[PDB]
Image (cartoon, rainbow, N blue to C red):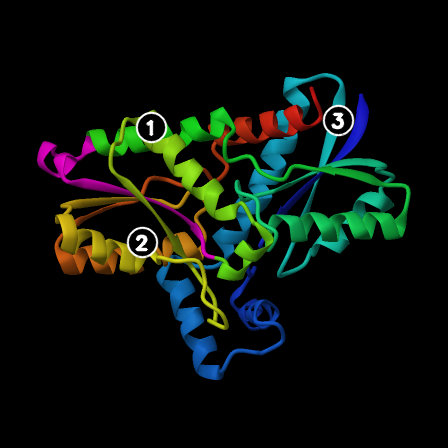
Amino acid sequence: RKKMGLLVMAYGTPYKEEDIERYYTHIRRGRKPEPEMLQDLKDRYEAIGGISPLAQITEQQAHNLEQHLNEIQDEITFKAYIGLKHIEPFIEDAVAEMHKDGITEAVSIVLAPHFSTFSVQSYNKRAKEEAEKLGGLTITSVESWYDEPKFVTYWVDRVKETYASMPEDERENAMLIVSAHSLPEKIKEFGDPYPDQLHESAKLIAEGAGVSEYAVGWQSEGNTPDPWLGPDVQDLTRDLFEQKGYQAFVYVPVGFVADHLEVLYDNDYECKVVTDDIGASYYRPEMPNAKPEFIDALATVVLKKLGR
């Protein structure tokens, strides 16, 4: 049994209400949010059911993956380490931990299926530079996994169930909106494949579920310096309805893997407000979270990367 480190990286989420300030200050490059901003951020977390369940998902995903990988093959024993971008344990901390435990070989994976220079590449770079600084630790990094058959099927099956559940009439006038986290539009100057990968994910899911009509949109953009990738899901819904009058909208935020704020609020609240206003039905299938089907897809991605 070869010992290998499994570095699972993610954006990060506060652990308790008192972390919101520092968590958002970090995301905003040092600009701590105004008292008024802080206050409603808390309100949003409360509306969605609370903060603590949020961070648990990432930990559960990492541990279930570890446990699953170690059961499906007999050559390697994986040890999972979580490295986050906006709250401890940060990426550097997780790498330092691995080095401390005597890990010399590691494989990394970001919990976001699509690659981006702004996101994934940045995480991978941080993980590798730290390892390099410490020395004696080598890391092979997965860059994207949106096209993993097992991951595509999870969403294909969820879309099928949803379309099957709606009345024939809504089923006749339904629109599938596939989305991911918006990023500054400037990434395109670097030839960033992020937009293309999202569109490809949308094609993969729609075709597998037999959906002829679907659209791609973005959500959760930032503090507008230069424009961010658009169109936003809120605007896209309005637009699409005024044009063809879709009686139902199914949101598949394929860019996200858990029941986090950007799904529970930006979709379940913000998009629902729009559908409620226009009198259309709102549908948003369950996120993969730590579901066995999902953990199996992640294990396969990691095994393929190592050629096992």
Q: Viewed as shown, does residue 297 lie left or right of 69?
A: left
Determine which residue is flagged by label 1: 207
C-alpha span from label 1 to label 3: 37 Å
x 26%, y 31%: residue: 211
Amino acid type shown at disc 2: Asp
Mark 2 surroundings within 10 Å by alpha-carbon count, few (fewer than 14), some (14 through 19), many (20 or more): some
Picture layout, residue 55 above or below residue 67: below
Q: Is residue 206 above or below residue 74?
A: below
Q: In which quarter of the image is residue 210?
A: top left
Kindly identify the residue that appears in the image at 45 percent across and 56 percent down: 182
Mark number displayed over residue 268: 2
Which residue is at a point 88% across and 50% down the rendered structure image?
134
From the image, state whether disc 1 or disc 3 is nearer to you.
Answer: 1
What is the x, y in percent for residue 268? Answer: 31, 53
Q: How far apart are marks 3 and 2 (CA)?
A: 39 Å
Q: Looking at the image, is 186 positioned above or below residue 91?
A: below
* Residue 164: % across, % down: 21, 29
Quadrant in which the C terminus appears? top right
Q: Mark 3 points at which residue?
A: 77
Nearest the eye: 94 or 232: 232
Q: What element carries label 2?
A: loop
Q: Which residue is more in the foreground, 139 or 70? A: 139
Q: Position of residue 167 (x, y in %)?
A: 12, 34
* 179 is within the stretch colored magenta: yes
Provide the residue span drawn in magenta.
165-182
Query: Would you say residue 27 is visible in this rendering?
Result: yes
> What type is the residue that disc 1 sits on?
Glu
Q: For numbered disc 3, what is the local secondary structure?
A: strand
**Three-letter amino acid code at the position of disc 3:** Thr
